[PDB]
Image (tube, coloured by chain):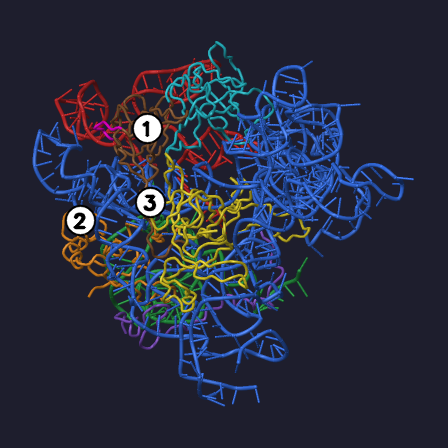
Chain colours: A yellow, B brown, C orange, D cyan, E purple, F green, G red, H blue
RNA sequence: UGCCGGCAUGAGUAACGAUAAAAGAAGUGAGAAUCUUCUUCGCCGUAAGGACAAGGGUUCCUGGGGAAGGGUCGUCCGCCC
RNA sequence: ACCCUCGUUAAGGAACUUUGCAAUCUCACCCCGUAACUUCGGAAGAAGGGGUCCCCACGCUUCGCGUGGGGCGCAGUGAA
RNA sequence: UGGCACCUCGAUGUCGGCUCGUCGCAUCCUGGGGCUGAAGAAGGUCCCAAGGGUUGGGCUGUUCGCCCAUUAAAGCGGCACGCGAGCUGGGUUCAGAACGUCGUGAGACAGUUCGGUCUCUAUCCGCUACGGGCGCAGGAGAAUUGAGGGGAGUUGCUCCUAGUACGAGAGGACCGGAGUGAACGGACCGCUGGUCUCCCUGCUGUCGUACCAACGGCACAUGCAGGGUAGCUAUGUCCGGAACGGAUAACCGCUGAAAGCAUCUAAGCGGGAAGCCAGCCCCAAGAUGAGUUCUCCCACUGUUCAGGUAAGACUCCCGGAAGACCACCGGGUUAAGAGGCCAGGCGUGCACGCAUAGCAAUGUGUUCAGCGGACUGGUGCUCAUCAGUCGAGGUCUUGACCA
């Protein structure tokens, strides 16, 4: 129920007396800015707001959202959820110790409506002769004339998935001197310079 | 989202070297009569010193370094790019004015053992 | 799919055999006219090579010589091209539009000086 | 790992031509004979069992001719890295004679062996192990 | 070799609601830096030939 | 489920032909990317050379104009005079 | 996306599958070297082994090879 | 396997094989349960619902089938015994020939065998996608809680109270535990590799420089041997189905009625693994069942008629590891966005001049740098003067409410 911040860059890092795997992420602290109550606006809530911009010549409407007891420029927004926490910044180095099983999430990868051969990874169908089919197609996917509405399945081409992947469990590395760093171990989603909401232990006991 | 107008890479290159503390050896010098040796594991400790009798060769790129460019012969070949970045290994050795083949990796040869493959690389055929 | 930049549409042997009878119309002329991409990835060649043109050596006249089959490419790069702008790193000729082909859509600039 | 698979010197029993093809396992180091075990994979590990194809034979001392029997293996050449920012791997390996029940007939291995066969319930592995 | 022929057609009714999901983007946005009025999507005259400074030619 | 004559729609998509590179200065003028005076490139050259055999009969020229054709079109044709 | 076309692989080399058509692999010249069968003229121009570029004491040298000291590259009719 | 011959001969082509497979359960392997002539190990039959899942070789055209080892086990009825708007024909079942008996001969056989073309411009219903818009009533950049549409689950194995309850002897649990694996969701580049069609070295043949160290055009759009970044994906690495509440079936009760005893008396309530509410994500309050917040323009008048004045969307210039277009992003100068130049790796590994041994092929030296397609960057130079489009102030009624 804590931090949230921009992906971008990974690498392999030392562990005990070896090298292992590792992953990395960058961050800052957009700061709350808004804080209401429980009377409309539903449950608890909050709204993240801030990173690295020049919102001046941006527009003259968002600049006013930016108004409470803080300054500087903001880039993105977003929210978190219910819970209790001070009114400071985003960072895994807040009040809750170090060494936590955070659970990141990612968007997508720069693709564009491709085959189910990818949506299924297996495109079986030997066709080393005839080439009417270049193996890329599943085939079959049909029956007789008793009705037929293509079901709602069929992961045919379309638009892939900037959607949330919620990586779950992904251990932390080390916390060093600096204005917050934060790293992990295990791919981590979000294409390169992602963002990631970052979320508390959800695994079901 | 992690791209705006800020250069944060002193973690990727700072915190990166915030843990290092070593001037490796950095000698690609082939065919040495003795060298470094892993601390092993096995029992409780019994930190022995007889991993592999290397010829020393190679470099790499950052925390990875496919060290081994050695293998042997009793077991046909057998390389296993070990991690240059570690604090559990003997602090190397270096010897040999070295007639240097290509340095770094090779992959070729490595089977052309026979005999004349001591510490040279030119040949007439 | 890929990205980054720097690609190739026109032939795959047109990367060391093209401007050598295309952008060669710049030594004695300069009325060069070739694509709204070629030129944009042509800068990494023209204003590019010049550091070994500042004076005059030999090796500084190799693929500076034979790379643009001509004479002015060397008999001018030394004391008339490099020094022509031997005070500003990159950024000189004002390549832009010109008036398109009328039919399809491809402009090709001109390149000049003064 | 893999059906056929061409290798080099085996148990040094006899001949320089061997085989393997079928895989068997149960996660033990020398139990006995039961109904089942495991091996829904597509290869092996290292200090496994693997119903290896006999194919050849040894001179004449305690090993038969056409023979046939659930042979074993030594090392492989697929996956796993030595953790120490490195790896340990061949592109051949050997076999060695190791009883169907799981009683490693280990006469006298010659040539380098493995160090990763010290978590594979080595027992009769690494003893007469030449190079390590 | 012929794959299921035309048979059914699509004259009127349809063939109407097909000039709207494209059409032409409709423009008339800008009208040149200073003099007269051309400009394109960020691009200098041929009139005075300029976005703000020296370029092109009458 | 006829026959011709015309309008059709498949629809503006598939396709411009063996995937055997081309840029440009300049002539012209109605604007010119594929003409023309031309330095650079490359494909064939036991060929996709030139002559004889059959054929088409008007190809070749002094050149000339787009109605139409060369499945873009064009101030090029061996279209048409 | 996919699609015809081309090339390069860790891990096994046909377990793939009706059967290595396809795919793709692969088969220099000189010398020495060479079977069961056989109407001995064959089956093999088989298998296999060394070289063939360069400075040189040197041929029928207006052109080959050759007893030798040696030169470049990981490899030498080396592309086809 | 069929009895019917009802429309299908203006014609719907066996079977099988890969892959897509998604349904049902009677359940093929878990689960909690009835019993077991079951001590344990392990089963023998039955009860309940889907939560999942179910191999590789041999032959065949194979449905089937048995032979080899596995597998927690290898299902049964789906679908014209799934389907060429996939291929395949492979058998055989199109015309050729051969055998077996036969018809007198021409010839006959779901008797046997050898080869033996195979479709076809996808308007579309529909489905996987992205856009043109319309929208619950002033116009807008964006941040949001939600029905719900999908994704959404399988399992052997060490060690431990385990050498115990049980067993007169071999051996070995109801609970869970950290632990090794599979086809199987993604991710990520920085452990492993390829890919690289132009950056280099190596070599034969041809030409252009007269000519040479030295280079280029041709050998798939790199000729041949090798190397290669930014990217991609698997063998690369990590994570994947386990807490727990309502309430099940199999089953176990507290009081035990009516037939004064008892049984889970359906009259009070509990224990019940997997489904179903839920717990991880997309979508999405336009689900017309119109939800909330940060934010911008206006105190005037003329074509039941009526203006001189906009900020947000945008043509866009140079660009994005974003792509057909395009929803998301970076500069338009109050200027560091692609390229050139520059510090540095990068790979061809010691470029060119010159002197020398001297027949000299070549070598040494100055140079582990010369040489370097998109690399952390820097330089605001090659480009950025400017210019345009919704030119506007909350519909009817009644209530909590304002002096």
Secondary structure under badge 2?
Answer: helix
Q: Identify whether B87 is placed above or below D71.
A: below
Give how far apart the Cα atoms at labels 3 and 2 are: 45 Å
Rendered-image quadrant of the C terminus of chain A: top right
Q: Is the magenta stretch mostly helix, strand or loop?
A: loop
Neighbourhood count class around disc 2 (C-alpha, 10 Å): few under 14, some 14–19, many 20 upward = some
- Residue C107 placed where, x, y %? 33, 63
Q: Mark 3 points at which residue?
A: B15
User: Mark 1 and mark 2, same subunit?
Assistant: no
Give how far apart the Cα atoms at labels 1 and 2 are: 43 Å
Q: Give the range drawn in magenta.
A: B93-100
Q: Mark 1 points at which residue?
A: B70
Q: Name the residue under label 2.
A: C61
Tell which of H273 and C90 is nearer to you: H273
Q: Earlier in the sequence, mark 1 or mark 3?
A: 3
Instruction: Output the chain of dot 2.
Output: C
Give how far apart the Cα atoms at labels 1 and 3 are: 32 Å
């Amino acid at each position: 129920m804590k931090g949230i911040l921009g992906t971008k860059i990974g690498m392999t890092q030392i562990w005990k007396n070896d090298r292992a795997i590792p992953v990395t992420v960058v961050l800052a602290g957009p700061c709350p800015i808004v804080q209401r109550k429980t009377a409309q606006t539903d449950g608890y809530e909050a709204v993240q707001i801030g990173y690295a911009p020049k919102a001046e010549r941006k527009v003259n409407k968002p600049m006013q959202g930016h108004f409470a007891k803080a300054g500087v420029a903001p880039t993105r927004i977003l929210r978190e959820f219910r819970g209790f926490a001070p009114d400071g910044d985003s960072v895994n180095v807040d009040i809750f110790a170090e060494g936590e099983k955070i659970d990141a999430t990612g968007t997508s990868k720069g693709k564009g409506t491709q085959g189910v051969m990818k949506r299924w990874n297996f495109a079986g169908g030997p066709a080393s002769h005839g080439s009417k089919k270049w193996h890329r197609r599943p085939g079959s996917i049909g029956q007789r004339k008793t009705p037929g509405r293509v079901y709602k399945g069929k992961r045919m081409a379309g638009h892939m998935g900037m959607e949330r992947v919620t990586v779950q469990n992904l251990e932390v590395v080390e916390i060093r001197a600096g204005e917050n760093l934060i790293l992990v171990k295990g791919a981590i989603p979000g294409a390169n310079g992602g963002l990631v909401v970052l979320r508390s232990a959800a695994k079901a006991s | 989202q992690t791209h705006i107008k800020i250069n944060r890479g002193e973690l990727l290159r700072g915190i990166e070297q915030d843990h290092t503390r070593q001037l490796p050896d950095f000698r690609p010098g082939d065919t040495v009569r003795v060298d470094t040796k892993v601390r092993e594991g096995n029992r409780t400790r019994s930190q022995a010193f007889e991993g592999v009798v290397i010829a020393i060769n190679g470099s790499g790129s950052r925390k990875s370094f496919t060290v081994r460019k050695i293998s042997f012969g009793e077991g046909v070949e057998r390389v296993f790019p070990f991690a240059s970045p570690l604090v559990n290994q003997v602090t190397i050795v270096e010897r040999g004015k070295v007639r240097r083949a290509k340095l770094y990796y090779l992959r070729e040869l490595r089977g052309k053992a026979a005999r004349i493959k001591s510490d040279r690389s030119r040949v007439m055929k | 799919h890929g990205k980054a930049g720097r690609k190739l549409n026109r032939n795959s042997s047109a990367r060391v055999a093209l401007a050598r009878a295309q952008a060669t119309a710049l030594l004695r002329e300069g009325r060069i006219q070739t694509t709204l991409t070629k030129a944009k990835e042509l800068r990494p060649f023209v204003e590019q090579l010049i550091t070994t043109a500042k004076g005059g050596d030999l090796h500084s006249r190799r693929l500076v010589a034979q790379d643009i089959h001509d004479k002015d490419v060397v008999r001018k790069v030394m004391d008339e091209v490099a020094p022509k702008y031997a005070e500003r790193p990159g950024g000189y000729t004002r390549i832009l539009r010109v008036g398109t082909r009328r039919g399809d859509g491809v402009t090709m600039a001109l390149i000049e000086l003064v | 790992i893999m059906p056929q698979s061409r290798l080099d010197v085996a148990d040094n029993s006899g001949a320089r031509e061997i085989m393997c093809i079928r895989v068997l396992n149960s996660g033990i180091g020398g139990k006995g004979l039961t109904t089942g075990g495991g091996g829904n994979k597509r290869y092996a590990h290292v200090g496994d069992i693997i119903v290896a194809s006999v194919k050849d034979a040894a001179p004449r001392g305690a090993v038969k001719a056409g023979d046939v029997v659930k042979a074993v293996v030594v090392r492989t050449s697929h996956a796993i890295k030595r953790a120490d920012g490195s790896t340990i791997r061949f592109d051949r390996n050997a076999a060695v004679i190791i009883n169907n029940q799981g009683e490693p007939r280990g006469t006298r291995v010659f040539g380098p062996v493995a160090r990763e066969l010290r978590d594979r319930r080595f027992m009769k592995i690494v003893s007469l192990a030449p190079e390590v | 070799a012929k794959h299921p022929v035309p048979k059914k057609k699509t004259s009127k009714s349809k063939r109407d609601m097909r000039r709207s999901h494209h059409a032409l983007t409709a423009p008339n946005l800008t009208e040149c830096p200073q003099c007269h009025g051309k400009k394109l999507s960020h691009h200098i005259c041929p009139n005075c030939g300029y976005y703000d400074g020296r370029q092109v030619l009458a």
